[PDB]
RNA sequence: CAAGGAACUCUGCAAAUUAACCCCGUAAGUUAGCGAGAAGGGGUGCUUAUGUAAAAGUAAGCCGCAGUGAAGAACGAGGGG
RNA sequence: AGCGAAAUUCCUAGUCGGGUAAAUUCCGUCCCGCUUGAAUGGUGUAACCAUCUCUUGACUGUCUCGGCUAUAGACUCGGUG
RNA sequence: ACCUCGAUGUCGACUCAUCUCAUCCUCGAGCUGAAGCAGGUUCGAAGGGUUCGGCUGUUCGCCGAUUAAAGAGAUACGUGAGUUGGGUUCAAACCGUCGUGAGACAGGUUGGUCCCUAUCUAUUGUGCCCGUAGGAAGAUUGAAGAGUGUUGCUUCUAGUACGAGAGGACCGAAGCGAGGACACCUCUUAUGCUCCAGUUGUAGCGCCAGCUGCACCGCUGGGUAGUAACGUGUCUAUUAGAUAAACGCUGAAAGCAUCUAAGUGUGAAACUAUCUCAAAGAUUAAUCUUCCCAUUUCGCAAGAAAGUAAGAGCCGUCAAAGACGAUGACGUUGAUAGGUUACAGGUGUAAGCAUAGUGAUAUGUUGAGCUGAGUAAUACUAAUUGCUCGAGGACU
C-alpha cells in the first residue's frame, strides 16, 4: 500500500481541479451598513434590527 | 483509543449542559455552539414551562441542575428566579428563547451561536 | 400526507374485547380454551398466573405459566385474540412490571390477593 | 433451531436420561431441528434397569424446547425445557411413561402413539 | 396487460386473526382513489401506457411547467405523476377508486423502495459470514478473505467488472410479490395487506396485480374477538 | 447478545466459570511434614431484643427478585510423561 | 539385568483393550527392541511445577451466527502538517 | 535450466473463490441379459447445486453419520501491500543413529518475532464539469445489461399396472419442506449510554427527608423511538420462442424402404423471452409532451441598457436521506426543527401528607409520578428580512 512513481504537475493540479471550492453565504446589512453572509450577525453587533452583540 | 483521547461522550455532554444551564440562569446569556445552545434550550423550555406550579417538589427537582458559581449559588439563583422571572413567560407556548448566529471561533473558526432571551 | 396512525385503532375497533378483564402480570387467572381438533369446540382451561402483559391493541400479548408433573408450561398468548375468554380469578402482587423469578422458584411463596 | 452436539434429556422412560444429537438426518444443511423432527442421537446416560447402554445411537424426536415454538394460531407456544423422546423407527415411541403432557404441533406428523399415551397433550 | 396498480402510504404494521384461527400479517396502507393523468396508445406515443396523477395538491405549490400542463389537460394538480406500461384503457383524467381495480382477498405484488441503509458491509449487503476469533486474525478479522484474481501474466491480474461490492445500501425500488389483499376502507381510503414490506412509513408504495397468483382470490373471514359482555 | 453449548483447532489460547468472612466437610496416596481453599457445601441486608468492653452470635420483626447488595479477590478432577 | 513400538521401534495407520457415534494423538497390554539398555547411570519414586500432555465438571460470541449501545478515530472543518 | 537470484511468499488451514466440463446430482433422451421395483449402458446436458464430526502441520487418508449429489480438473500446488502459522525452516535443548568428535540425520523429543500510510490501474458505490446543440419541466424509452433460472418430501393418484408369489408401478394433481434468497418489525428476542425503576456504600448537597457524583453508565431489572434476527412474510412457479440429444411424417437415391435430400414437425433443470431492477454520456446522446421566452439601437450580428417571469443555485429549518457528496422536505405566503400542548407509551402508585407499628414498613392519600426518541395539533422561537445565475431559437 505505497506509491511507486512521483507525479507530473499537471495531473496533480487536475486532481486539484475537481478539488474545486465554493463561496461564502451572503446577505445585506442595513441595520448597520454592511453585507454579511446570509443568516448571521452583521459586522456591527446586530443580527437584524437590534444589536445582538457588543461593539467588538 | 491507544490510551489517548476519549473525546466526547454523553456524560461529558450532559455535565456541560447542566453546568451551562446553571450559567445562563446566572447570566441569561451564553456564547456557545448552536448544536449545544438549542440542545440545552429544549430542556430549558421544559423547566420553564414546568417551573410555574411553584411547589417544594419543584424545588427538590430543580435542585438537580446547579453548582457553585463565581456569581450565584443554588440558593440565590433559585430564589431570585422563583421570585420574579417565571410568570412573564407563563403565557407563551414554548420557544422561550433565541439561539442566534454570530461569527465563528478564532480558536477553531467554528460557528459561535449566542443563546439568550428577553421578556 | 395526513398520517394520523389513529387509523390503526380505527380499524382495530372491529376485533376488540370490549370488557378486557384487568389483572397483573403476576395475577392468577384462568381462560376457557377453545378446542376444535377438527370439530366441536370444547373447553380446556389453562389457568395460572399471567407472567408478562403488554398492551397496545391487537398487539396486546401476555404469558401464562403452569407447573404440572415437575414440568413448567410457559405459553405466550395475544391478549386481544379471538377464541380467548378471559377470567381474572385471584390477584397477585409485584411492584415490578417484568420479572422472571417464579418461573424457577419453589412453593409456599404466594403473594396476597390485593387488598 | 436445534443441531448437532446439543445434548438433552431422554423424556421417555427406556433406561436412559441424557442423549445428544450425532446427526440431524435428511436434508443437507437443514442443520436444525424442531418439535416433530426425528434425528439420530448417541446416549451417554443409561441405567441397567432399562434396556439401553450409553453409546448406542438411535432415533428420537424433540417434544419440548426451552426456546419453544410458535403455534399455527399465534399463541406463542413456549417451554422452559428442551425434551426429547426416543422412537423405534416409527411413530411408536421407545419410552412410554409420559413425563409431562407432550407437545401438540406434532400430531399431524404422527406420533399419535404418544399423543394417545397421555391423559393430555401440551 | 390488466396491471391494476395503486399508490399508498405505509401507515401501519400489526397482526390480525382470521378464519382457521391463524395470525395474519397486517400492513396498513393509506390509499385514496387516485386519478390517471395521461393514456397513450401503442400507436399514439408508440407504446400503450398510462401515467397516473396522485397526491393531489393545490395548484401553485408545484413547478409552473407541471401545473401549466395540469391545467393544459385540465386535471387535478397532484404532486406525483408516475406511469406504467401495458395499459391505456383509463380515460383521460379518470378519478378512480381501486375497489374496482382490486378485490379483497386476491394476490398482488408490492413495489416499495426499501430502507436507505447508508453505506453497508458485504456481510449485510451480499450477506456473507464473519471471521473467526482464535489462532490469530488480528485487526483484519473481518475482511473479504482471498480476493486474488490472477497471479502471473497468465492468470488474470485484474478485477471483475460489475463486481458485487458494498455501497449505499437499501434505498432502491424493489417489489414484494404474492402478498394477499386483505380488506378495504374507501371511507378511510385505506387497505390491509400481508407480508413484510421494504420501505419506511410516510412513503408512497406502488402495488400491481400479482405476477404469480392474480387468478387466486381467496378469503378466509377475519374472526372478531369472540366473547364480549 | 436470546438458545444451546467447544461442535474451533493441530488443540478450551482466548474467553469465561472461581473468589471475602463465619461455619461444615474433604479422596487416594503419602515417606507421614502433607495432600487440602483438596473434594464439596450452607449462612451473610437492615429494625428490634439479646448477646460483651468490643463481637462473633442468638431469637423476633422488616424489606427486596435477589443483602462480599457496587470495589476487590483460587475455577476443578482425574491420566500419563 | 532392566525397561521396552518408548522424548530412543524402519516396519508402523505392529497388536490387544480402554479411550473413541466414530479417535494417523492419547492411557493400560502384548516385545524378533533395524543400534533400547544399567554411571550422558537403569528402574521407579511422595510432593510440586508461567513443565509437557490425555480425558473431563463449571464455564463460554472459541463456535455456530449473526449483531446492538457507548466512545478512538477513520468521516467534516480549520490550522499545523 | 530458458528466465527473475542488485531477491519470484512457495505447504497446509480459513475465506473469496472463480472458472473447463471429459456432469456426481437436479432436466431430458436413447438402448438393455430393463416382470415391476431396483438396474445397467449411452449421450445430450454447467442453470444451479453437491454436508458434518473424530484421529494426524497437512488437504489428500481413514473413519462415523448421512443427504440430490457430498463431481472432477484449472487458476504461481489461485488466493499472507486477505489472516494465522501447524510443521517440516532461527539460533536453543535432548534422544535413536553415524562420524573418533565438534558436526550431520525426509529421524524424532520442546517451543521458539508475518513491514505497508494505495501512485496508478483494476474495480465498487457514487458526487461534480461539460455534452446531448433556445432556455426551464416532467415523462419515458429501452442500445446494451444484470440476476433469479436448487431441490427434496406428505398425500393421493394406484397395490393400480407389472409381475405371481411377495413385491411394486407409468402419469398427473394437491400440499409440506429443507435450504436459499429480497424485504419487514406486530410477535419474539437482543440492543435500546439523557425512559423508568429498585439500587450498595463513599465523598456531596447546615439536619430528617429528598435527591448527586463516584464506582461498567456501581450493581439489578424492566422498558418507550429505533436498531438489529433467532422472529415473519415473499420467493423458489407458470409460460412462449429457439432448440440438443432424441422420435417424426412424406419421400428419395437404393422402383423399396429411408426423420433429409425438397417438403412437414416434435422433442432437455441447458438457450431466448416470460419476472425484477437499472439504464439514452446508448457522443447511439434517441423519444413524448409541459412551462417559459422575443422592450429603440454596436460588433466578420451579437445584445450597448431592461437579463425569467421558466427555473436553478447559494443561505437556512430540516430527515426516512445521509461518510461527505448528495436525494428529499420546506423557509414565514412557513408548520421545517424545536419549544407549547394532549395523548400514547412503558417504568409501573411518586414525593409530601396523616394513621399505625418501635421500626425495619405498611397504610391511604395514588394507576401515582415520571417519561431520550412516538403520535398529532399550537407561529411561541429560529427556518431573514437576501444575493447569484437564470429571457430575445444564431444556422438545415
Image (cartoon, coloured by chain):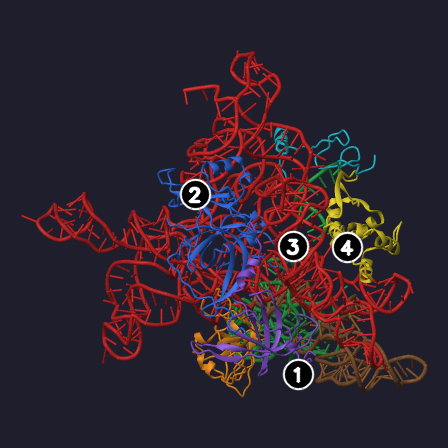
Chain colours: A cyan, B yellow, C purple, D orange, E blue, F brown, G green, H red
Tag 4 residue: B47
Nearest the eye: E58 or E175: E58
Tag 1 residue: C107
Tag 3 residue: E138
Question: Are callouts 3 and 4 both on one chain?
Answer: no
Q: Chain of mark 2?
A: E
Above or below for E196 versus C92? above
Residue that protrudes farthest toward the bottom in the picture = D49
Report how far apart the C-alphas of labels 3 and 4 lie in the structure: 50 Å
Q: Residues within 10 Å of mark 4 (few under 14, many from 20)?
A: some
Question: Are callouts 2 and 1 both on one chain?
Answer: no
Residue D67 visible in rendering: no
Above or below for E65 versus H234? above
Tag 2 residue: E93
Question: Are callouts 2 and 4 both on one chain?
Answer: no
Report how far apart the C-alphas of labels 3 and 1 lie in the structure: 52 Å
Amino acid at each position: 500500500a505505497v506509491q511507486q512513481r512521483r507525479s507530473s504537475k499537471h495531473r496533480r493540479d487536475k486532481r486539484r481541479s475537481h478539488d474545486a471550492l465554493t463561496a461564502q453565504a451572503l446577505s445585506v446589512c442595513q441595520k448597520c451598513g454592511k453585507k454579511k453572509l446570509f443568516h448571521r450577525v452583521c459586522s456591527c453587533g446586530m443580527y437584524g434590527d437590534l444589536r445582538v452583540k457588543k461593539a467588538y | 483509543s491507544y490510551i489517548n483521547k476519549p473525546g466526547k461522550t454523553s456524560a461529558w455532554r450532559v455535565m456541560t449542559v447542566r453546568q451551562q444551564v446553571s450559567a445562563v440562569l446566572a447570566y441569561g446569556k451564553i456564547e456557545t455552539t448552536l448544536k449545544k445552545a438549542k440542545n440545552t434550550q429544549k430542556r430549558l423550555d421544559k423547566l420553564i414551562t414546568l417551573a410555574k406550579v411553584d411547589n417544594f417538589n419543584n424545588r427538590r427537582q430543580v435542585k438537580k441542575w446547579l453548582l457553585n458559581t463565581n456569581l450565584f449559588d443554588v440558593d440565590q439563583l433559585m430564589d431570585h428566579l422563583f421570585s420574579k422571572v417565571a410568570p412573564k413567560y407563563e403565557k407563551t407556548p414554548g420557544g422561550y428563547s433565541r439561539v442566534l448566529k454570530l461569527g465563528p471561533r478564532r480558536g477553531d473558526a467554528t460557528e459561535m451561536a449566542i443563546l439568550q432571551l428577553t421578556d | 400526507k395526513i398520517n394520523k396512525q389513529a387509523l390503526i385503532d380505527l380499524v382495530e375497533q372491529k376485533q376488540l374485547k370490549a370488557y378486557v378483564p384487568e389483572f397483573s402480570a403476576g395475577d392468577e387467572v384462568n381462560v376457557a380454551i377453545k378446542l376444535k381438533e377438527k370439530e366441536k369446540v370444547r373447553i380446556q382451561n389453562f389457568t395460572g398466573t399471567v407472567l408478562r402483559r403488554r398492551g397496545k391493541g391487537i398487539s396486546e400479548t401476555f404469558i401464562v405459566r403452569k407447573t404440572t408433573d415437575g414440568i413448567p408450561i410457559e405459553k405466550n398468548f395475544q391478549i386481544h385474540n379471538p377464541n380467548i375468554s378471559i377470567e381474572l380469578k385471584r390477584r397477585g402482587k409485584v411492584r415490578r412490571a417484568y420479572i422472571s423469578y417464579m418461573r424457577e422458584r419453589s412453593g409456599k411463596a404466594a403473594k396476597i390477593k390485593e387488598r | 433451531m436445534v443441531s448437532f452436539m446439543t445434548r438433552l434429556n431422554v423424556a421417555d422412560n427406556t433406561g436412559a436420561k441424557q442423549v445428544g444429537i450425532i446427526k440431524v438426518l435428511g436434508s443437507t444443511r437443514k442443520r436444525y431441528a424442531f418439535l416433530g423432527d426425528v434425528v439420530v442421537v448417541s446416549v451417554k446416560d443409561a441405567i441397567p434397569s432399562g434396556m439401553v447402554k450409553k453409546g448406542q445411537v438411535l432415533r428420537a424426536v424433540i417434544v419440548r424446547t426451552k426456546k419453544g415454538q410458535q403455534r399455527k394460531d399465534g399463541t406463542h407456544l413456549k417451554f422452559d425445557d428442551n425434551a426429547c423422546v426416543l422412537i423405534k423407527e416409527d411413530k411408536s415411541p421407545r419410552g412410554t411413561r409420559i413425563f409431562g403432557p407432550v407437545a401438540r404441533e406434532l400430531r399431524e406428523r404422527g406420533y399419535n402413539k404418544i399423543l394417545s399415551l397421555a391423559v393430555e397433550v401440551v | 396487460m390488466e396491471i391494476r396498480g395503486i399508490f399508498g402510504v405505509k401507515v401501519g404494521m400489526s397482526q390480525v386473526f382470521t378464519t382457521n384461527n391463524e395470525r395474519l400479517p397486517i400492513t396498513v396502507i393509506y390509499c385514496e382513489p387516485n386519478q390517471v393523468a395521461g393514456v397513450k396508445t401503442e400507436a399514439k406515443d408508440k407504446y400503450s401506457a398510462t401515467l397516473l396523477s396522485f397526491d393531489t395538491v393545490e395548484n401553485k405549490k408545484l413547478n409552473k411547467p407541471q401545473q401549466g400542463f395540469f391545467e393544459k389537460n385540465n386535471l387535478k394538480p397532484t404532486k406525483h405523476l408516475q406511469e406504467i406500461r401495458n395499459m391505456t384503457g383509463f380515460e383521460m383524467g379518470q378519478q378512480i377508486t381501486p375497489q374496482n381495480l382490486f378485490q379483497v382477498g386476491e394476490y398482488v405484488d408490492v413495489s416499495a423502495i426499501s430502507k436507505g441503509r447508508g453505506f453497508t458491509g458485504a456481510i449485510k449487503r451480499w450477506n456473507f459470514k464473519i471471521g473467526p476469533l482464535g489462532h490469530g486474525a488480528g485487526y483484519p478479522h473481518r475482511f473479504q478473505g482471498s480476493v486474488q484474481a490472477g497471479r502471473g501474466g497468465a492468470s488474470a491480474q485484474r478485477v471483475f467488472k460489475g463486481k458485487k461490492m458494498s455501497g449505499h445500501y437499501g434505498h432502491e425500488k424493489v417489489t414484494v410479490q404474492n402478498l394477499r389483499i386483505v380488506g378495504f376502507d374507501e371511507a378511510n381510503m385505506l387497505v390491509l395487506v400481508s407480508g413484510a414490506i421494504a420501505g419506511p412509513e410516510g412513503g408512497v408504495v406502488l402495488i400491481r396485480t400479482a405476477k404469480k397468483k392474480p387468478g387466486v382470490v381467496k378469503p378466509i373471514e377475519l374472526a372478531v374477538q369472540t366473547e364480549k359482555a
